[PDB]
Amino acid sequence: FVNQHLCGSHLVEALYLVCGERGFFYTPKA
Amino acid sequence: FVNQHLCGSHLVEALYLVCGERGFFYTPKA
Amino acid sequence: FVNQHLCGSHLVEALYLVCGERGFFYTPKA
Amino acid sequence: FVNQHLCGSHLVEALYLVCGERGFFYTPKA
Amino acid sequence: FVNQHLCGSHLVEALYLVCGERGFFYTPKA
Amino acid sequence: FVNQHLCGSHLVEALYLVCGERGFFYTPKA
Amino acid sequence: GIVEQCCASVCSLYQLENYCN
Amino acid sequence: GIVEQCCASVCSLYQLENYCN
Amino acid sequence: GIVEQCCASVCSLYQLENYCN
Amino acid sequence: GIVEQCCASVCSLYQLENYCN
Amino acid sequence: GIVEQCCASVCSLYQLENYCN
Amino acid sequence: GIVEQCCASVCSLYQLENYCN
Ligand SMILES: [Zn+2]
Ligand SMILES: [Zn+2]
């Protein structure tokens, strides 16, 4: 696997693919 | 707004849209 | 719901989610 | 180009690609 | 069809739509 | 990482994510 | 869960707000 | 409609051009 | 237009409803 | 092929690496 | 390459056909 | 955070695993 530049919904897509059924938490700063 | 069938990555894309900066948790097992 | 920065196909995705079965018109300037 | 099954948001993504600046109308009911 | 500005995964999406079942090769420079 | 059902454009999106700069080949017929 | 409500069945954007932090 | 032609059945990029403004 | 505003600046889902049929 | 393994059945990210150039 | 041109500049769907199998 | 780093800089899939449940 390689390093990736992920922004916006592209990140949540990556998270969904990596975590799958385990689920995940999306916690951005604001 | 209308009702819709949202599955897989499409479901997390919608969560990202609705929640935005607030962030969210995707938990299939729950 | 929160404010969103939507560009390109990301906007048409948002439109599809908000309008659903009602359908929508995508009219950009050019 | 080849034929393809295009449903839901995938269909509007294709319309965005094909139409571009011209814009389009997505009307399920029609 | 119109000219498009395609970056990242947005390009592979376009390729998938244009080539379909024929398949394609994604060869970026690096 | 977990196992997952990946079809259509979702499959090529995952390949793009995993392969990145290396690039990939999508060959349905093979 | 979210999946049973939005994928098996249908759900609204308002329902999705229940999963925001 | 577009849905019946592109989702139920299959359709080409050329057919999609009928829905551009 | 909304297309421009949503991308140049920012826009809300409520504003996007104005474009539904 | 890739489709039979990742769409018909399930597959891991590691398996997808077999299709990188 | 197409990857670069489509993103740095602009490209057409006809140009993308050159990459199909 | 990962959200920032992945977009401002770069991040790996292994780093993203830290966010799974
Ligand atoms: Zn994007
Ligand atoms: Zn899909």
Image: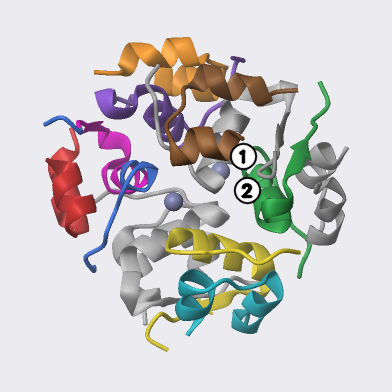
Chain colours: B yellow, C green, E purple, F blue, G cyan, H brown, J red, K orange
- Residues indicated by labels 1 and 2 sit on the same polypeptide chain: yes
Asked if B19 appears above or below K20 in the picture, the reply is below
What residue is disc 2 on?
A: C13
Quadrant, the C terminus of chain J: top left
Chain ID at mark 2: C
| Residue F20 visible within the image | yes
Q: In the image, what residue type sits under mark 1? A: Ser
Q: Position of residue B16 (x, y in %)?
A: 59, 65
Q: Is F26 colored magenta in this rendering?
A: yes
Q: Label 1 CB, ligand 1: below 8 Å? A: yes
Q: Is K12 colored magenta in this rendering?
A: no
Q: In the image, what residue type sits under mark 2? A: Glu
Which range is magenta?
Answer: F13-27
What residue is disc 1 on?
A: C9
Secondary element type, mark 2: helix
Q: Position of residue H7 (x, y in %)?
A: 47, 40
Rounded to the nearest whole Å, what is the CA distance between mark 1 and mark 2?
6 Å
Asked if E6 appears above or below H8 in the picture, the reply is above
Between C26 and C2, the one nearer to me in the picture: C26
Chain ID at mark 1: C
| Picture residue at 19% right of the left edge, 48% below the top | J16
To which quarter of the image does residue J12 belong?
bottom left
Crowding at dot 1, Cα within 10 Å, few <14 / some 14-19 / many 20+, comes out as some
